[PDB]
Image (cartoon, coloured by chain):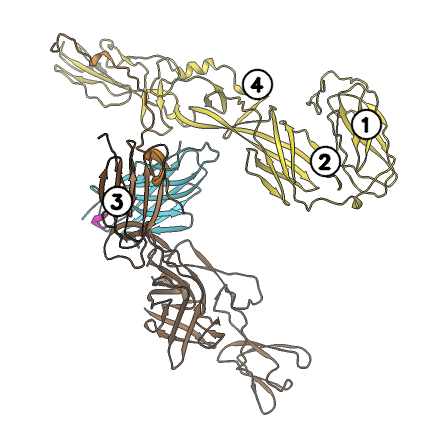
Chain colours: A yellow, B orange, C cyan, D brown
Amino acid sequence: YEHATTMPSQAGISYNTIVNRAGYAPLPISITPTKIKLIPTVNLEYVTCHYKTGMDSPAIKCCGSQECTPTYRPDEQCKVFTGVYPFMWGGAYCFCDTENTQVSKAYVMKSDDCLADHAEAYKAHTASVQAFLNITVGEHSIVTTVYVNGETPVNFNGVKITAGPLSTAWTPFDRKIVQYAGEIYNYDFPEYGAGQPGAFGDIQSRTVSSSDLYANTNLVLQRPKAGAIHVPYTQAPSGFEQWKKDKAPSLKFTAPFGCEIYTNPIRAENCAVGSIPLAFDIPDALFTRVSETPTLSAAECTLNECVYSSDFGGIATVKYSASKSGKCAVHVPSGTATLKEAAVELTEQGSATIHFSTANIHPEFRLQICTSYVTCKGDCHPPKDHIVTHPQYHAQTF
Amino acid sequence: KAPSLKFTAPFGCEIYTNPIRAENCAVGSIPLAFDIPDALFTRVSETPT
Amino acid sequence: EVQLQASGGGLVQAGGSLRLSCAASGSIVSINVMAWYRQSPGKERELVAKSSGPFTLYADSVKGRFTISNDAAKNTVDLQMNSLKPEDTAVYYCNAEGLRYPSGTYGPSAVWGQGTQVTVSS
Amino acid sequence: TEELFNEYKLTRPYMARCIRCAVGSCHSPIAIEAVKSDGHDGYVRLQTSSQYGLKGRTMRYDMHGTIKEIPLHQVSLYTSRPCHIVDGHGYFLLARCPAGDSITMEFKKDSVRHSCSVPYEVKFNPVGRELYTHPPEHGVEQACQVYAHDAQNRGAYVEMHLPGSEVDSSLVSLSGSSVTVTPPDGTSALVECECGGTKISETINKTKQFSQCTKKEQCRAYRLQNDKWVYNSDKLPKAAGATLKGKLHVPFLLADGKCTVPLAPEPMITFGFRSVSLKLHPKNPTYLITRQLADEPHYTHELISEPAVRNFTVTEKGWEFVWGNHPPKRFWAQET
């Protein structure tokens, strides 16, 4: 048997319903989502980190000339100058006065700290949604992970539940993301091969251990000071460090809908947007005959206490007269009031107490008891606390 | 068993095994853009006219 | 992205015994297949070893001499290579197929490492 | 190789029921467990009761509790024409012979023929799109799947348990007036029955005469075997104990190798204005696939075993086909 239902996407708050066959006792269903995660299609593109100015020993030739040999290291710069008069601790390295030549060749290499400190680039799109559900259909309670796309049902006791796709394809992430130290930021980094000096992406590497890197640090060699063997070099500061000092606030606190971010793998969860539809396929063996369940007669409502707060604040005493003692489900067909419990145990000639939540000053709602209906009515009082520490359990009717 | 995609696919795309992929079939046009440095250019007078 | 890193090989005399290792890095949790292929100069690519879980398979010209072992926990394969003949010189590549990314953005299926050179001298 | 033979050395031979030993239902040491046929060139693997190779090429089989052996070149099997035995190790055999409907294997040690026939299909699979019945003398190379001739420790394993307490009506004998149980040399056994009260006794290489139960047909002396093992098969009872205690690996696992496959005759082509006619003279039934090089394929596939003439229309976008195992042929026309 095919049944359709809808669920506002939000964890914690439970959901109660009864499927009512025209000639058999209603079958109860309870649903509780635990975690609703949303994982994107994310493909890694590159990685960056601190760089280190690789500088060999200066190549000095004394009264002669030299040439440049390109090692083809990334962003290599080579230069030769004349008219050098170097010194050493033990006097003069040379005796020549002029014609001396010195050659400098400089480059960049990845810092030793690349493994533990490195910012990753990511291209995100195509969010897929997963969920953990705690569902009980006909006192068959289960906790299970389910693919809530438009296929992939999960079956237990013959009951086949299918959670359809979301009504909204919104995602908190932008197309290009940057990851670092477990924090996530939506940033527009320049793409591979187009890095610029003094900004993010000056040094470029396909992977952590690619061993082939592109670089634009704009390294410039300079004439060393006279009477000293050394090589002065000038370059823009680390754009990674400039971005480190800039660091706009994190997505964990900037995202709308209050979406929390964890990255063991990149994912976002526990934030309410849209609705998830549920499709039940129930086998015909789970339906029980009416005579095998208690049936009531002359049942009446009374409203004992009212507080139309966020939490359940309506207490109702229902007085009944039963042919049998046995548990049955109680349901409110409309959204006027939402009950707290999925089932209530029932004596022969006792009275039942029911907790519910409503936002109506003058509620008048029809409850469905084991096989009959009763019409509870009354007025209700405002709350006392201005703010609470939990969300709303009910809807806001117009 | 039915005929293979390498024997019934449109546009004559050839499919290989190791990465699932297709090659050598004509569809559409690739736009290309070039940024050429001035170093490779030559003066008109230096070329026969 | 997922990659394969190959280590081992070198120049040795005939009759020696070496080990070739290939390791997988990236966003992977389980691997369905890992195999070895050899490419000699002037010829085409051929298979040598074939390991996936407990089962193993060997070619016609490699039976009884080379042994393949796989470690899915480390996602590595070790080809213990013995009884060298002059025809065994080639560049060896390690291949991985049927990759199950850990959701794990689905991506390319197969991968190919750079490989290692094995040369044997009479 | 002994490193791998010692595994199957210490298990057992065993006997089992047979549908036909040339005389009705029967009990034979030549029961066939199951048949698997997936190899391309017709290689088949058989799982018999008696084990092989234990000595270069010999068979060893049980007979009413006693072991015997015979050289391998005296046992023969067939489906429709005589088959051929290649190699045998452990419980398994590798054979090669064409398709059929049943497997019938037999031998003749004394002047009495032992046989079993079973209805398990064997299927001959042609490599490629050019079907045949016997591989050709010449052709081209392709990668198919064949069962390897080598026996090496693969990851495939089979299960093995302790033997059941098989009964033997021969041991119980009659004295002047009594029933005597006479176990063989150095074997243990267990005697059961209810002729008076209830009796379940055990004997360890001792002959026992029972004063009561002074007749033949009543009751039973089961054997005991401890240092030997059996395969988990339906034709043996399971003794007490749900333990398993070990497993063994299988030889002749499927492998990949180069394979000879036929080549079809070169088709005679005649051209026309946007049309091409094909004359075709197959030696054996062959496939044809033809498709256009446009967005609509209109792929057309045929099996042909007789000569015929087939005309096709080719547009500017292009035509392509394969006839048999040849490389694809693509034809591209112009204006005329």
Asked if the residue at tag 1 contacts the one at tag 4, i.e. Cβ–Cβ closer than 8 Å, the answer is no
Residue ID for mark 4:
A256
Instruction: Give the mark count.
Output: 4
Residue D278 disc label: 3
> In which chain is the residue bearing label 1?
A
Marks 4/1: CA distance? 36 Å
Marks 2/3: CA distance? 71 Å
Residue type marked 3: Leu
Residue D189 visible in rendering: yes
Residue A360 as seen in the image, left or right of residue A241: right
Residue B44 location, quadrant: top left
| Mark 1: secondary structure | strand
Residue A305 disc label: none
The lab-note entry on whether marks 2 and 3 share a chain reads no
Residue ID for mark 1:
A315
Residues shaded magenta: C84-90
Give the percent coordinates (x, y) of residue A335.
73, 25
Residue A18 disc label: 2
Give the percent coordinates (x, y) of residue C63.
30, 54
Residue type marked 1: Ile
Marks 2 and 3: which is nearer the front?
Answer: 3
- Disc on the earlier residue, 2 or 4: 2
